[PDB]
Image 1 (cartoon, rainbow, N blue to C red):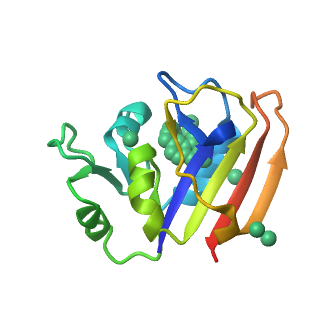
Image 2: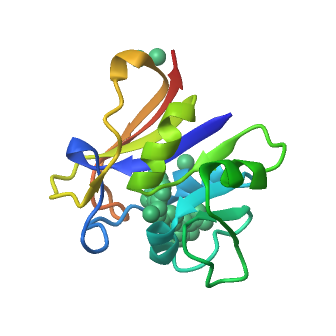
Image 3: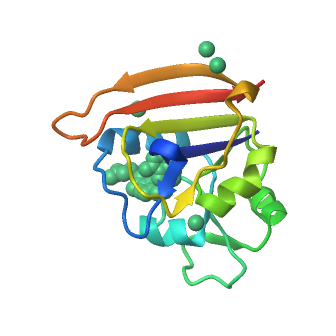
Length: 159
Ligand SMILES: Nc1nc(=O)c2nc(CNc3ccc(C(=O)N[C@@H](CCC(=O)O)C(=O)O)cc3)cnc2[nH]1
Ligand SMILES: [Ca+2]
Ligand SMILES: [Cl-]
Ligand SMILES: [Cl-]
Ligand SMILES: [Cl-]
């Protein structure tokens, strides 16, 4: 099964010209909880944003240009990315925009963090149809001493 995991500001904003203007360690802990010991597929801009390989996960970079880091796996097609995951119960697609757009039709599950932030977006999560998805988990949190915005965790399963 292929799953997508993303953090969405209002209007499904996922990326901006520069780093996103929030500080959400609790969302990064949720990201880690749901990706640990699973292969993760990402695009090159997300790879640069993270800075280093994500620990405890097989890091696969989908890109048309050859790779510039030996600590991860570089693939050039969606099918090569999936084959590089081997035989695993769940593949995690972690963005960004174009990578979400390519993997959404194959995905059966979405892990979404909805962030109460009004920002002008550079890239957006795909306009999925909520009629077509079933929320099986939702958990709301206010901003606090460590987290700058209110956020809601959601898991959605393809109806
Ligand atoms: N829910 C969600 N939130 C995100 O911030 C997110 N970010 C990306 C792309 N960007 C990033 C940026 C940083 C890290 C990261 O550093 N994660 C660490 C935990 C952070 C920490 O320990 O300080 C990890 O080990 O997973 C992951 C993805 C893709 N899907 C997401 N999904
Ligand atoms: Ca429900
Ligand atoms: Cl968590
Ligand atoms: Cl990307
Ligand atoms: Cl629902």
